[PDB]
Image 1 (cartoon, helix red, strand yellow):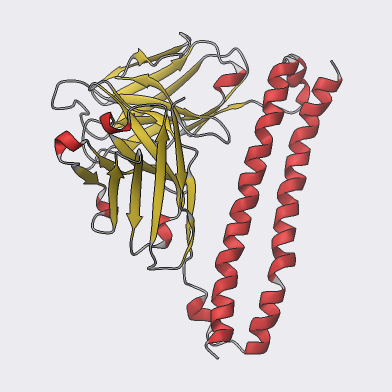
Image 2: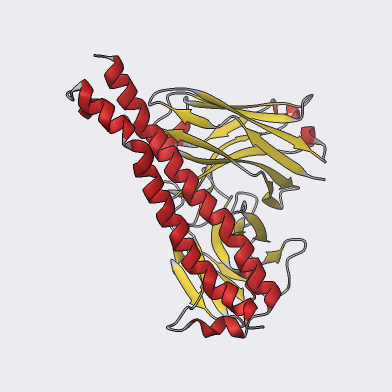
Length: 173
Length: 165
């Protein structure tokens, strides 16, 4: 019955803002410390913030790379923990997990959520397409969809070549 | 200075039934002020959130089979799988919660040796072969969604450029 469900991720432009939400169910939310953990293919797993209980005055801790930019908060009445994110940069892109500590000074993240994705665009093409002609910008825009479909089909074709050896093994049984 | 967790190896190709040993080295002592060492081992299966396996260096979490073993002290810690099963495949992360900021290791991918011919799946059971097949779909849709999110980041500066004309 213990479940954590995140929400609020999406696409952000460089320097933008975003607020994530994580609702809890199946346990007494007010008794457990909560955290935010993010994952990126480049930096791996990264702990973001920690919020304690009302007895500890809802004390918070942050990683240095996010201090003064991110703010963790909780509402025990709604059994929810939030993460307000300001001046988002491309490095902040990743899957953001909301986690709960086991407690009793024994163990940490025993229950994670499914995670929400935060995509912060770089802004490099902004300082390179500005000198382009409007006619070439329109042709570049109309070529995006077939370009994306080409990379997607490569992934599907790769996964077909990884499924057939398995599928042939169950067949040979 | 923050605690750096260095994991070795990056990849561990094994066959089912093999022994696995994953090493995690910390840049400094990770003994909490209360005397406990909060070295933890997590396993992320393909398409799922990380799950806690070992807590406090050597203690198995609830529901963790006894083939998982954790050990170590000082700056060197080791996770051992006595006999690797299909359900153990994934990425293993070491984690320290003794000093703020809490840091994770780089990760160790426990994967199947593919060799030169794909007859090693003949010795597999159908149920484990089906789990491998069921796991490939979330990995594909993730890789596809990264492509979709990437192109969304390439379309917006175009419209803004035509906009600013």
